[PDB]
Length: 595
Ligand code: HEM
Ligand SMILES: *[C@@H]1O[C@H](CO)[C@@H](O[C@@H]2O[C@H](CO)[C@@H](O)[C@H](O)[C@H]2NC(C)=O)[C@H](O)[C@H]1NC(C)=O
Ligand SMILES: *[C@@H]1O[C@H](CO)[C@@H](O)[C@H](O)[C@H]1NC(C)=O
Ligand SMILES: *[C@@H]1O[C@H](CO)[C@@H](O)[C@H](O)[C@H]1NC(C)=O
Ligand SMILES: *[C@@H]1O[C@H](CO)[C@@H](O)[C@H](O)[C@H]1NC(C)=O
Ligand SMILES: [Ca+2]
Image (cartoon, rainbow, N blue to C red; front, side, top):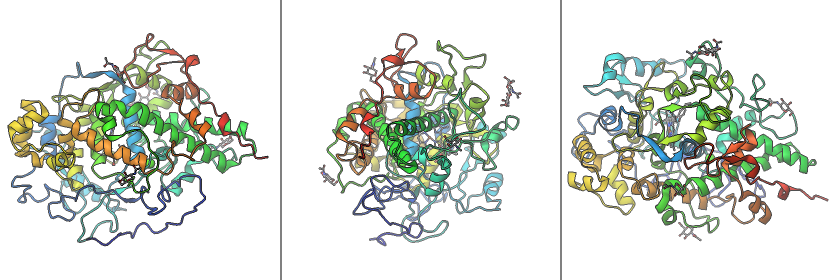
């Protein structure tokens, strides 16, 4: 066994039993073991961590040491050989809107974050890793293979630092290293409100007693709000353009400004919250600040649950959706709602769905201006193209009228992310999201592909012919084999994503199984699930049953023409209808008859 509960960083676990609202930290959801699904605790291990030394080291740390008799391939070599492609033609998913990709990143953020090791204060370590590419302690550089273009213009490696782990920040033994999930495992709208009280309050507007979320005072969007700027220096949003000097936004989740479209979706959320607190004020004028905030927060987290589970998940899982997420049967206190470590990798499937460009569209959904279509890499940490360039309404149109990239066996990840990714405190648009993912798998001591195949009640190929038959691809199988030398060594991220898509779905069997379980666990282990009897009133539930993303757009943007089904591909003007004919969220069921 292990020390039953290592817990030096998490002390305070005091719970109010009457409380009708979720805590910001996730704590007190589970009564028998409150810390389940709470921010700042270890990610769950569905299977024992697999580490080079069986403690904290990652495979590929010691050159001599092999995994199952073979050396594991360099993350970047796998990337170049398998992940990359040149031709962006015929790569768009015909039946998925770009919103599909976007919602997947939103939901993912709400659920898990495993941030890097924070051990360098007035230290050159972030630069000693980057400048001289020397692996040590938390620094775990992604080295370039022999034939690599980036070797010629960038250096010997790409900087990479290991993720944070519970108890000691830098040293520990002998139990296996466990990474931290810095957000709440629950689909609770954390990304809008925060997972810490320190952040939660800063995000709030406590000046007025209207329970509104703090907005921007330096800029507006045709009378509509923008999230507040985060005034911390240095900002990468200012670094990308030093002339525009527009900093990153401040949201409930740290990563909000990574790409313009996510920041965009973050802006749509804050608005719907403020819009909700204003309607509650009008029907319940006796309700105070905190109460207006909490009830609005309660409704938004319910909205994210319905969209994700009713509209989003069935089109990710497709045929495999009932097999894993059968109709709700109520809260089950024995269900672990913690995000597992492997899900933070299973969910990365979304990377394949990211297209190489983003567009801006006018009322007739036509190119908005001369540069309307821009390359994705010019949008990493770019908040200025929203403030100084037309607001969100044009971007929210792109999201409805354009397509997500379709995952493709010979075209998995676009170069915008493969070669051109920007990372804070590193200057260049010259990083690789694919290499990073694979590096992270090893950093998190991930079990190989077959361990996971076995875990899901699926076959475990040991030959080239076996792998060919599972992937339904000769050449993909051969490249993987030549690199890994065995399936048993294939990193889960590239292994799960290499499998053909399930019928009516956008992922393979292995991912549909992993994604499948996790989502059902976060629905069943949630005491505050919107459908759990007693959370909302019988009537409130009938009002919430009508929410839509279309409605979220109409309610919080000046667009008046939207599809009925926001995630499927939709063309203008045919697939578009007026906002007038769209179900509204009636808030009458929230009337507080106190007298
Ligand atoms: C830029 C990036 C994106 C869009 C242009 C993007 C998009 C997605 C989608 C669509 C996802 C799911 C449907 C998704 C999931 C997860 N991501 Fe990814 N993402 C961009 C960039 C990054 C970067 C950089 C990281 C950090 C990777 C690391 O190991 O350091 C990243 C991570 C993740 C992630 C793991 C979250 C966690 O638990 O830490 C997903 C589950 N994304 N992204
Ligand atoms: C930096 O941001 C500035 C300011 O928004 C961008 O400047 C503008 O872009 C074009 C000119 O090419 C004009 O439409 C705007 O009027 C410009 N504004 C100003 C103040 O010059 C500039 O293009 C951005 N630069 C980079 C490298 O991203
Ligand atoms: C598109 O997806 C929807 C589900 O989101 C489905 O009902 C429809 O049949 C699909 N269209 C095609 C051509 O497969
Ligand atoms: C707080 O709310 C008041 C009243 O609506 C508003 O005037 C003020 O601008 C808000 N402050 C912030 C920082 O959002
Ligand atoms: C509750 O979870 C337990 C443990 O996973 C499971 O055995 C049981 O079937 C669940 N209860 C219901 C009503 O589904
Ligand atoms: Ca959460």
